[PDB]
Image 1 (cartoon, rainbow, N blue to C red):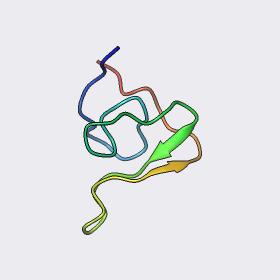
Image 2 (cartoon, helix red, strand yellow):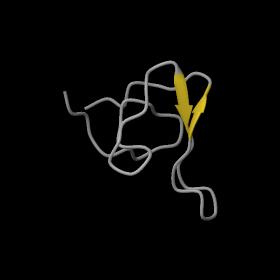
Image 3 (tube, helix red, strand yellow):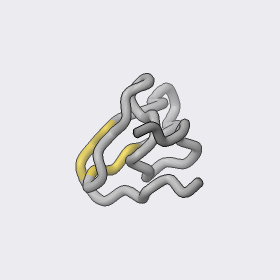
Length: 49
């Protein structure tokens, strides 16, 4: 399957780290002064369409 490019910090099923997708149940953190992506644990949200 293929989702889409993230657009808000806290997503999961999106292209977080590079072109690879994270995994529901985690928590990605976008834009953060140099930190464009980081698949960290926590509770993210299924990037809607």
